[PDB]
Amino acid sequence: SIDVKYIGVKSAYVSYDVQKRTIYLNITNTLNITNNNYYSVEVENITAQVQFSKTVIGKARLNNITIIGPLDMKQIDYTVPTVIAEEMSYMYDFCTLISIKVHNIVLMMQVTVTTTYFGHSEQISQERYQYVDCG
Amino acid sequence: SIDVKYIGVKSAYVSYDVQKRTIYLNITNTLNITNNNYYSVEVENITAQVQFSKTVIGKARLNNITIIGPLDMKQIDYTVPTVIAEEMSYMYDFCTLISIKVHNIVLMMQVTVTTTYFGHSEQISQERYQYVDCG
Amino acid sequence: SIDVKYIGVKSAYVSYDVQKRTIYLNITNTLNITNNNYYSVEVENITAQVQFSKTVIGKARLNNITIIGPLDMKQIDYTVPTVIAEEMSYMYDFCTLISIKVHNIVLMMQVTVTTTYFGHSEQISQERYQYVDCG
Image (cartoon, rainbow over all chains, first blue to last red; front, top):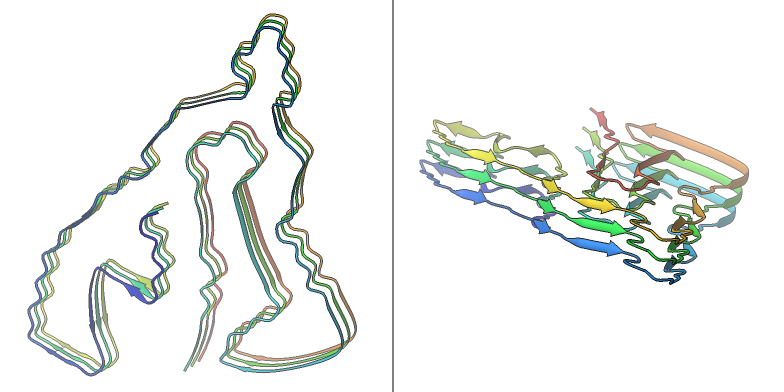
């Protein structure tokens, strides 16, 4: 909720990059840094009362107070039919990165059917650092 | 919730990168750093009352107070039918990274059907550092 | 919830990288670091009362107070039918990384059907560091 960075190559606070045929003579670097971070997050002071029927007296009658009726979920449901008569395939792959007909699914249910949740929740995902290097 | 970084190559606080045919003579680096991090997160002070029928007196009658009725979930349900008569395949792979018809599924249910959860929850995932190197 | 980094190659606080045909003469590095981290997280002060019928007196009658009715879950359920008459396959693999028709499934249920959970929960996953190196 504060510092969510997607960085491409490198990250630094103080950085030097000296490359590619350069001359770097008799310099004098002098840093005097003071970097302090005082995070104080999410400090909560909650005070909740959650009743469904508080203080019913005197010959009353209640019925179907909270009814979360018929429920249906069908999250990932997909059909990929394929009807072929004659198929011929040729793949000549060199220093590549292929993916054919794969199925990558990620599903994360944090707080599903419940009642009266308090506190904090968090869901984080980051995947598939794939890589190919040829010389 | 504070520092979630996806970094590409490298991470540092103070970094030097001196590469690729360079000359680096008689310098004088002098750092005087002061980096302090005081995190104080998620400090909660909760006070909850959760009743479903508090203080019912005097010849009352209750019925079907909380009814989470018929429930159905079908999360990952997918059909990949394939009808072929004649198939011929040729793969000539060299220094590659292939994936054919694989199925990568990840499913994480943290707090499923329940009642009156308190506190904290966390879900984190990061997968598949795959890699190919040829010289 | 604070420092969740997915880093590509390397991580450091102070780093030097001196590579690839460089000359590095008579320098004078001098660091004076002060890095202190005071984490104080998740400090909770909970005070909960969770009743379903508190203080019922005097010839009352209750019925079906909390009814989590018929429940069904079918999480991972997928069909991959394949009808072939004639199949011929040729694979000439060299220094590769193949995966054919594999099934990688990961399923993690932390807090399934329950009542009145307190405290803390955590789910973490990170898989499949696969690798191929040819010279």
